[PDB]
Length: 572
DNA sequence: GCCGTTTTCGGCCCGACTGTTTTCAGTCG
Ligand SMILES: Nc1nc2c(ncn2[C@H]2CC[C@@H](COP(=O)(O)OP(=O)(O)OP(=O)(O)O)O2)c(=O)[nH]1
Ligand SMILES: [Mg+2]
Ligand SMILES: [Mg+2]
Ligand SMILES: [Zn+2]
Image (tube, rainbow, N blue to C red; front, side, top):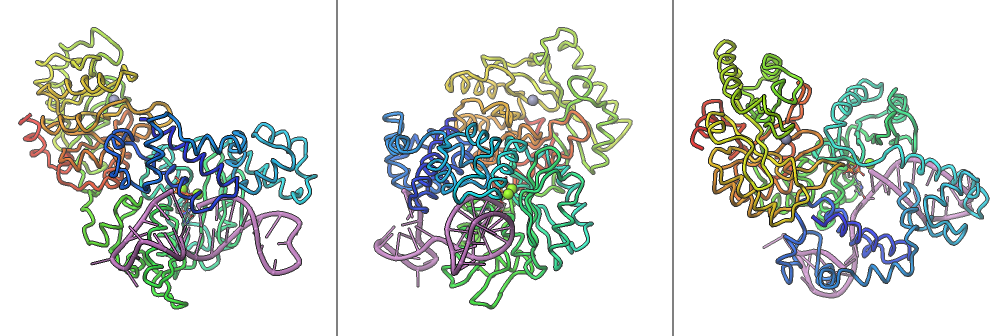
């Protein structure tokens, strides 16, 4: 991938232009193209390999954001970006990333106190300079200090799974606040986006001041950036930004739509409303002053001539077009999943025994659970050897016969060597119920080699699932360089399923690689990669990722019952 | 700079919070 650089490059063209006072809509052309490319997990040049007049087609991208890309790879750099660089100091971009700052304030600060970096800004307030500026007051200076200090505690975006459980605690607390008729977790959290920038809570209330004052009073709250009658922005005792939005109960449905987004999806709907002479806000759909919809989401979407769109689809990735023409995808649902196909145990890196896993699986209402432990490669040991994997399969057999349902499947997560060979001999793989293969080494391999390595792993006829394929770690490590079309092509042809690993720091396949695979007709496997019984609660996230990728119950191994899973497995 | 089951040109989402703004601009979701 190289989206991460080019996402920053347009983001910079937009910001430098925004500083120079450019056409705001041209500015927004870049900002959007920045957001979609960074969110794009399928490598861009793999899509750009066919660009040309078909680059005029991509997503949120037109002809002008193409000849610049024609230029980009032809010459390594876009003149527009370089032209803007000469007019706008590199450090002013950093200053206007500070929440509350923006173009006009960054410019005033530059021409006023010559501030052109965070380091300089930091010095300016500590010294107390901005409280002297002509127009920039002492109150407006405290505003900057807030935003400057509050940008730091909230470091990176956080994986959804890292904050999920906390989010539900806060939700249950907000539902118990006086004045709160009804509350819900919206924003990116509700769309199951693999990472979040904050947590966005909507509240139905008729005494909104009470609820906001009640919300900020929660013990996890550390600071308050902004606080009004209807909304508040706060940061927790751990850095995580949390926003509250209050709306009257009559507009609850329009409030859910508003706070759930995405921005881009929301803008499609409002733009649509304009075509039909209507207005869409948080308060409802309106024809003139007459509110035609608001109480619920269903009827709000109906007001725009649309069926209800599930939150995970709301990324303006074709869900609106598919809603107009009445062909929304049928989506997987959590109760349809009848087991977890990658959990670990005390046999290797897990914290749990078979009894502990079985008990956890039964409690959740699972039909089965695959106990897949690491191959020797994880440590490179010689005893634990391949010999005693048979006794492990034997021990799990007797466990099933004595306990009954749910059933433990004897599995294994087998390392893929740098050449594509597997960490376990074939006779060991032959007698395993579930065989997962995955990469835990040599990530910097060139695209072509990493493809060959993966392809040879798929030629092994005992392989059932290709586990967390990209090998990424959210915040720690990028995806491996690989031609994923060829890899999914091969896996399909060999009947191997691709894994959506719901473990909080993996979330791999990502939504849009998952949507690609499933679109090609591949089978899918869902797991949590659990090392403690807590982790089994991540199935929700793999499902949500499945949902984001327009994936239904068809060709998903977890929706099969115990018997049908074994058939599928026993028939290689 | 994108973009068209009412458009290939003329628009481009809508409203809350903050500050020194006496009538609204800046920045944000
Ligand atoms: N109409 C409209 N809605 C917006 C705009 N910006 C944000 N929203 C809505 C959509 C989602 C909701 C929360 O905004 P966030 O900034 O939290 O974005 P998010 O979608 O939750 O993602 P993130 O994980 O980055 O927070 O507010 C906008 O410019 N216009
Ligand atoms: Mg959010
Ligand atoms: Mg937010
Ligand atoms: Zn693994």
